[PDB]
Image (spheres, rainbow, N blue to C red):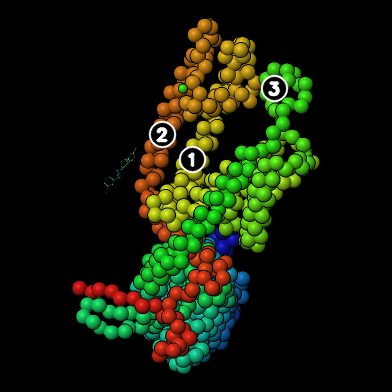
Amino acid sequence: WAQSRDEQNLLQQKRIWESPLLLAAKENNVQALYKLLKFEGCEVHQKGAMGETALHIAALYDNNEAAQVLMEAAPELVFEPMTSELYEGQTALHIAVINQNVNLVRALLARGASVSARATGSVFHYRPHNLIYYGEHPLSFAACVGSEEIVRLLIEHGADIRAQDSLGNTVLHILILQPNKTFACQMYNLLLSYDGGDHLKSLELVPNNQGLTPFKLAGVEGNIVMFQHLMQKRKHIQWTYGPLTSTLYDLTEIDSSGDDQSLLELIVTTKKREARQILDQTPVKELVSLKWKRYGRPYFCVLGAIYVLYIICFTMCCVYRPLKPRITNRTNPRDNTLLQQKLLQEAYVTPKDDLRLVGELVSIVGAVIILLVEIPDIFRLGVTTILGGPFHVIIVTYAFMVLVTMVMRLTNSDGEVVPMSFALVLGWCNVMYFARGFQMLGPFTIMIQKMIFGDLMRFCWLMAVVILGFASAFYIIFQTEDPDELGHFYDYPMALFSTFELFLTIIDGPANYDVDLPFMYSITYAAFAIIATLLMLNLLIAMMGDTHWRVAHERDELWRAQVVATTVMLERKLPRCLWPRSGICGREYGLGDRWFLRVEDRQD
Ligand SMILES: Cc1cccc([C@H]2CC[C@H]([NH+]3CCN(c4cncc(Br)c4)CC3)CC2)c1
Ligand SMILES: Cc1cccc([C@H]2CC[C@H]([NH+]3CCN(c4cncc(Br)c4)CC3)CC2)c1
Ligand SMILES: [Ca+2]
């Protein structure tokens, strides 16, 4: 798609090279353009490719000596914005502020220019293909390029500090998205110097269109530099006891007060890898440790002891399935037949089956309770880098499978083990979710997750590629030999199964010492062993070897997040009689109704 602007920028320079007026304005030839405006009166209001003016060109290629003439010969071009869609709304002041041309900006204000010129051009939007996002106002441009002299001159001419963009962002919301956090921190405080001054209606309370104060946005963006610079307005010093320093934190726009207004709600839902780096700062790291030590760790282990026993009961009733003989004289049709089906669909006898019946009634409510607490979370994606994604799928597919096994219990089939088997492994594989905040196997469980999707999925595709060539060759060689003393590949499905069974050295390999096997097998099996058993398989060890310590730190950082994120989940879906709010009420004491956190440190 980028060809448009590429062609347009090429079509731009073509028309500049074509029309001799803008060619002189681009190259700043004041002696030549005077011959055009007055002698052979040139069309002054020429509109180029992007609906631009000749003044817009002199501001681009910083030629302030030529634009001085255009202001003295036509001082109304300053009010002309770019008429194209790419640069709609952009004026000559924006380019002069971006390029930081002081005497050009200082002369534009001597002739009047809209300091609120909403540059709504398409390339000014906050998009990935747009390399920067300096906002829509010339004050944001001056603050983005980091020029105090331009910022105050716009304030000296009535610039709007709290001017929101299209996305509801003020001008502070844009500074956080900038890379140069070192110098932008100075610009932020300098920009706040022109605040309304009152205790209300300040810029740090004006939220994004999506409801994000600048303090909240810094956490989602992982801008630790701008984040800690915003903490000084909120933190409170208690006393100076030598090296010690008791510090009080305003704890307001951080702790989970209401619903989505929690700051930790954004850290756990975002995908930005630098947001995981936020919960190590001096207010958050201590709080999440307190919320996890008390209340956090115990309440989770209860659900662990609750859920683990719930699966044992379901397993205890699954292992005690109904029992019936064959019922049919089909004992020999296809000698390979070996089934012994289950019993009546009613089965109203009640000796000790009433003991197994109550467990089935225990297994149905746990599934619908899961559905009654997880189906209300129909949030798109958010599942399988993410945290509790796969388990929710494991849990809701387990619950749906048992709800099928209850429908399968009646009316249909004979021994519906399809919903019995799925709801058994998933029920036990889900207890790996209750790892997480458990010291030693928390980073373990996220590592095998980061390994089942990465190196294992790389290996599984190349593994399936190999066996299909051999299993077909194995079936072909053994679609003509006896399946009674060997026949590991009697039908093509078992050919694939027995060949795949040999990729992992599970079975013993076909090798009967009473037959003259097709020597193609002896050759095909040897090449199958060298490639698959050591070259392909031992390299999986080496592939798991390198990519382990490469992520042996991000896994722990992910583990702290999934410990903190799980600590956040309980505080929401649990009531209030248990799990009280962290901190101390600001009222009664000197403050009022707010909450504060006590933290001491140690200098040197
Ligand atoms: C901490 C944590 C949270 C969520 C998931 C996990 C891992 C273990 C459980 C899951 N896997 C995959 C799904 N499932 C399965 C079962 N049978 C065959 C196949 Br393929 C797959 C169980 C194992 C996924 C990765 C860890
Ligand atoms: C099969 C297997 C299992 C586990 C590890 C390995 C090797 C991978 C490379 C690793 N070591 C250390 C990481 N890295 C390093 C080397 N020197 C100094 C510094 Br600090 C770091 C590379 C060497 C370990 C040895 C092989
Ligand atoms: Ca063996």
Distance of label 2 from label 3 (alpha carbons): 41 Å
Counting residues from the start of the chain, the first of labels 2 and 3 encountered is: 3
Q: Can you identify the residue that label 2 sits on?
A: 539
Query: Circle 3 is placed at which residue position?
Result: 337
Q: Residue at x 56, y 46 (%)?
A: 312
Q: CA distance from mark 2 to mark 1?
A: 12 Å
Is 368 situated above or below 315?
Answer: below
Question: Residue 368 versus residue 79: which sits nearer the camera?
Answer: 368
N-terminal-most mark, 1 or 3: 3
Left or right: where does residue 589 sit relative to residue 133?
Answer: left
Q: Residue at x 50, y 78 (%)?
A: 213
Question: Of helix, strand and loop, which one carries label 1?
Answer: helix
Which residue lies at the image location 51% right of the left edge and 23% below the top edge? 507
Nearest to viewer (mark 2 / mark 3): 3
Taking the image as drawn, is residue 400 in sight? Answer: no
Q: Three-letter amino acid code at disc 3?
A: Thr
For disc 1, the neighbor class at 10 Å (few under 14, some 14 to 19, many from 20) is some
Under 8 Å from ligand 1: the CB of mark 1?
no
Question: What is the three-letter code of the residue carrying label 1?
Answer: Leu
Q: Amino acid at mark 2?
A: Leu
Residue 568 at x, y = what percent? Answer: 50, 66
